[PDB]
Length: 236
Length: 236
Length: 10
Ligand SMILES: *[C@H]1O[C@H](CO)[C@@H](O)[C@H](O)[C@@H]1O
Ligand SMILES: N=C(N)N1CCCCC1
Image (cartoon, rainbow over all chains, first blue to last red; front, side, top):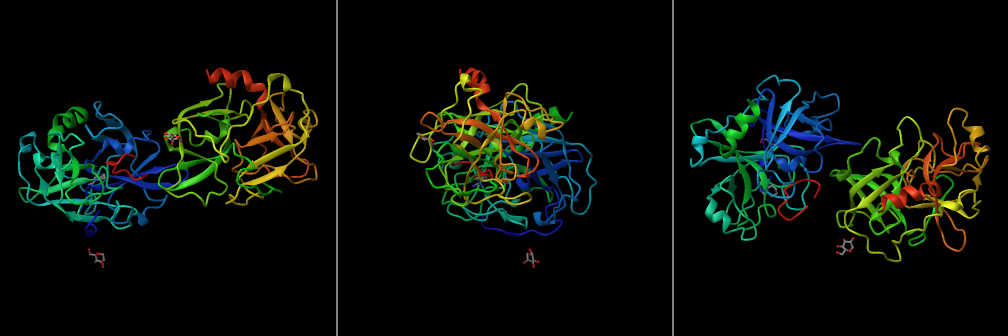
């Protein structure tokens, strides 16, 4: 994250590191526990490596440094990427992951609530980004989970700050007019969460942005409320 | 290479390193540029990691040190392993990598001539093996490309040493009985080039033999002259 | 890796 600080154990108990094991293992993507067997991330995280054997998912951890090979992994029973997702595009950037084994919930490992379809036009005032991405452009993966509060930029004002690219209603933008607060490389698939009724809700999934925290270049996030029928369909 | 010495920038411009990139990068194999879009290498270089969008190919570099994010790298569009190759056995050990974008030849990066089908049984005499492999058993990957010359040993002299392994007309052997000069780990898929009529031509591809220059343990190489049919058939 | 890619490799 650009322009944030260490999180604590149990602040963000839904956040997971997705890792790839080839010759060596490494963090690539964030995601969110939404149920015992279910993790929600971005489609672009599996662009290059769509083989689920290869992937490891880790929860209740504050630093990647605390993950070895003797650490229990959740593994992909099933990888559901929205059919409409095209491998080199920003649309339909969302994937569901069924785990082989249901997770045991703890102080440190909890699911986040999803919004109603009814929450589509709701205005959130208190929104946070988390992950182990870069703190700067030309940065490097962090050991300690980062967090940052970010204001939602309404969709029309976000469109006009990206003339080249096309902002959907199924996208949601966050950032300051200048600002150093934003998601970066390695924050892919991580949650934008907002507090609405005193509880946390996954409002967005880190998707794409032009640079990290550049002046007037807000981050763009898959808007989860808009995929709630897709989520019920693929989870039953 | 074992028994080798520092090659020199331009000495072997067909030589490429084959590397697995996630965030990190690891030199795993060598190959030979035979075409703007074509690299020839060993099938067993992709047994452990058969996923293509994880591989990177670097040509016209002398050291792996040279490489950072700056350094441009070809990517696999198609990976064509020999249909009769079997991980159990070391026969038909040959693979063609089709590069995404065509290569732009220089002093440092040029193809190499394939042998002709009729060249089978020709005895070549000015034979070189190149690669970044180990310089000793249980050694480590080399920063700077290593060249070494080596005599061929004909089949039936070779097949004597490989009591349980079948050495056939589709293979060449090369090494010194008491010589201790050979191809070690990381040289697999790398070229065995023997200068003949007047130019260097790829005669064999580094294949197998657990051991590096054990006395009386000559390197086995896929005999490129016996897959000319296959190679041209696969370059429609 | 385009300009918009938030993805780690690049
Ligand atoms: C060398 O030349 C082409 C020309 O576009 C490049 O685009 C490509 O990088 C290739 O390797
Ligand atoms: N939020 C920003 N800036 N992003 C989202 C993650 C991909 C890189 C750009």
